[PDB]
Image (cartoon, helix red, strand yellow):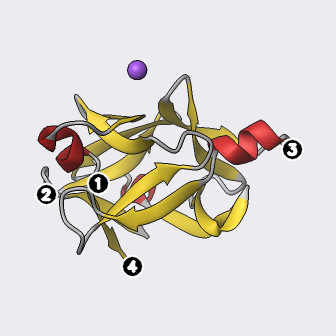
Amino acid sequence: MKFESSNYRGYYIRVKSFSGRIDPYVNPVEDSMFKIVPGLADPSCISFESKTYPGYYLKHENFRVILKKYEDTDLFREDATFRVVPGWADENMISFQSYNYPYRYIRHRDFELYIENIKTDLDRKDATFIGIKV
Ligand code: NA
């Protein structure tokens, strides 16, 4: 799957140097592509596996969304697990709630990805995505 930003259309979640951001015209476009597996800490949740780096998952660390090799720890699995919810800015779209930090959501901010509290209208828009099956 791919994930487009809804307020920066044509921008996609991608990994650059093992760090999550949103970019247009992702090159190599495979950096924008993930396998969606059951949540490592909860199968009613989701986890994001790298397509180019199998066994690496998107995960938050110091509230920054990064890519990191799987580790056999509860903290890693929790850091790597997100609940898909109706979009903050648009219920026809999606948002990603952190499993171990329930009041923090994946959002972009100067085109980097974090998990942060969603308080304002711009917060909601920065945290809203369109899943695209590829
Ligand atoms: Na903070």
Quarter residue 52 falls in: bottom right
Dot 1: what SS? strand
Residue tagged 2: 9
Separation of marks 1 and 2 at Cα, in angstroms: 8 Å
Q: Along the polypeptide, which appears first: circle 3 or circle 1?
A: 1
Q: Label 1 belongs to which residue?
A: 12
At a point 13% along the width and 50% down the height, the residue shown is 8
SS for tag 2?
A: loop
* Amino acid at pointer 2: Arg
Residue 43 appears at what percent x and percent y? 69, 69
Seen in the picture, residue 105 relative to 82 is either above or below; the reply is above
Is 129 left, or right, of 101 in this rendering? left
Ligand 1's quadrant: top left
- Residue 72, horizontal then vertical, whole percent: 87, 44
Spatial CA span between label 1 and label 4 = 13 Å
**Secondary element at image label 3:** loop
Q: Earlier in the sequence, mark 2 or mark 4?
A: 2
CA gap between label 4 and label 3 equals: 29 Å
The residue at which mark 3 appears reads as 72
Q: Quadrant of the N terminus?
A: bottom left
